[PDB]
Amino acid sequence: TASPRALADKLKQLAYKVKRLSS
Amino acid sequence: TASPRALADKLKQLAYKVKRLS
Amino acid sequence: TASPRALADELEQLAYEVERL
Amino acid sequence: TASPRALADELEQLAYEVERLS
Ligand SMILES: [Zn+2]
Ligand SMILES: [Zn+2]
């Protein structure tokens, strides 16, 4: 199954996408 | 360190806010 | 860019994967 | 309200905590 580091990597990648949005 | 359940809870909370971004 | 709804869906899925650790 | 940048910062902090799980 996916490791904690793998799950955290997807969370960080998702954060990068959220970051791109404007308020 | 923070439990999986505590971290999942905060992530679900965050998802609620992300989904309501305009 | 990905929609807020789409990004929230991915985040919810990851939350449940974290929960099940 | 909190900007997307602010929500993303919180998500990065949560990811660092997830990294410490087993
Ligand atoms: Zn705007
Ligand atoms: Zn788009």
Image (tube, coloured by chain):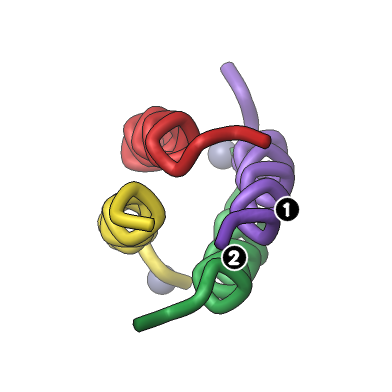
Chain colours: A green, B red, C yellow, D purple
Residue B21 in percent (x, y) is at: 43, 37
- Whether residue A10 is visible, yes or no, is yes
**SS class of the residue under badge 1?**
helix
If the image is split into quadrants, where does the C terminus of chain A sit?
top right
A2 or B19: nearer the viewer: A2
Using the image, tell me which numbered label, if any, was put on residue D16. 1
Using the image, tell me which numbered label, if any, was put on residue B3. none
**SS class of the residue under badge 2?**
helix
At label 1, the amino acid type is: Tyr
Name, please, the residue furthest toward the top.
Answer: D1
A13 or B4: nearer the viewer: B4
Residue C13 in percent (x, y) is at: 27, 59
For label 1, being within 8 Å of ligand 2 is answered no
Q: To which residue does mark 2 refer?
A: A8
Q: Are marks 2 and 1 in contact (CB under 8 Å)?
A: yes
Report the chain holding disc 2.
Answer: A
